[PDB]
Length: 233
Ligand SMILES: [K+]
Ligand SMILES: [Zn+2]
Ligand SMILES: [Zn+2]
Image 1: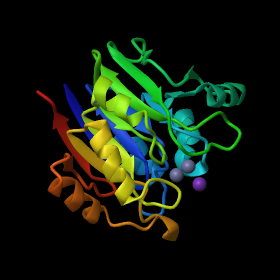
Image 2 (image 1 turned 90 degrees about the vertical axis):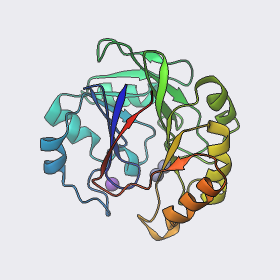
Image 3 (image 1 turned 45 degrees about the horizontal axis):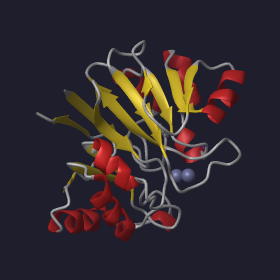
Image 4 (image 1 turned 30 degrees about the horizontal axis):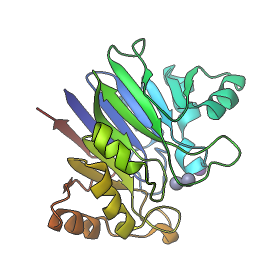
């Protein structure tokens, strides 16, 4: 199985997993992006939009993306209610076992995870694990501090690639993201949610050298607009 992973700055990603395009917290137009919304829409196919929580830095350009592409959303129940009432089409879920998304693509599932953070009045914040044929490929942590159930995610699923926030202040710092990496058992970690604004300034290369000197995993510091392909067998 093949995962083509594009980073757009902040916590915005496009995950292509065997010819289905899944966007997560798609603030394409964040301050560090090198991609306009026009560029994104020409260059990526969007089949699903994952929203981890309701902060605007994460919802981002979701609504316009969904209007222009026809893509459905995937999100926690409260956000599903708010967006369904606003006229959008999507799948709602909650924290637990994966949702079966066969209609989107055969064998695809996504589970919502805990996250120690906030989400205005729109339910609770989440992370998201993308499965194919029962295997956890990508865990996008949303915004979060440490959460003890990260250990269960490691043990039960060991998602291959972990997208983890490292900027501090509003989320785990580097130090906490290190412990998280240990708990979650990724093969590779892409750091996110850093440098966009002063309170979240952190050095992703500092993160890298500590995770790797600990032999905890490989860290792929991505650049806004960069794509990287991963195979796991
Ligand atoms: K915004
Ligand atoms: Zn947030
Ligand atoms: Zn955020």
